[PDB]
Length: 50
Length: 48
Length: 50
Length: 48
Image (cartoon, rainbow over all chains, first blue to last red; front, side, top):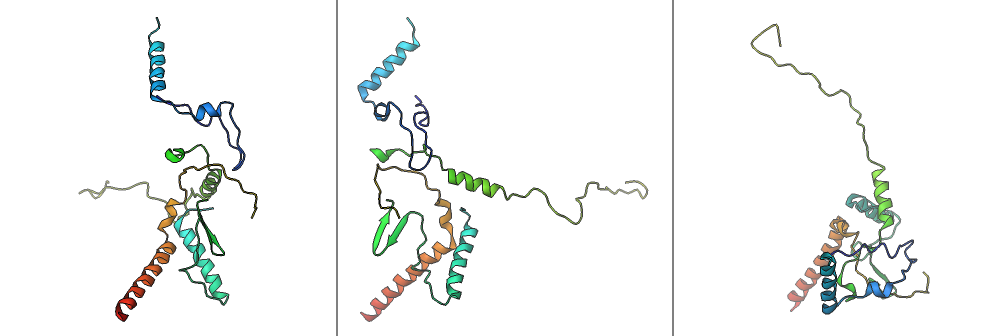
């Protein structure tokens, strides 16, 4: 599994000024074991259509 | 503006040569030249 | 937890400027007294042809 | 020298100055202090 590039959400202009994305709290969060299992379920369902 | 060793050595040698020719004596053992550590008036700071 | 992974999301523009300034001093040509040898001769037991 | 600082959080970053520390200046700075520690140790051992 590969995460997207971090530079997409936020861009830096100078050393003290940066832009903020709309989903910072969700981007900064980390999954738990059960959430990881649910993600695996999502991908398994996607890869077998019907 | 550089990271080459030979340029930095010549710069330091120029500083010490100048302060020596100026008449005073500057000890290379106490003189400090660092990126990340800052000291003044018995106050010390390391990496913020 | 915060300092667990190394971050690369902030590019060092000063480093790039220093690199370009250093590259600007690269030399391409050479000044020589005698051009390089382009033709050579193999000698054999003959005294008339090489 | 601004006095209006405020602090966000900690971070870890690569060090751009890593290659510079093979310089002669830092080597002599270290070697002065090794001589200074060793001569003091010798004097302390000799007196006692």
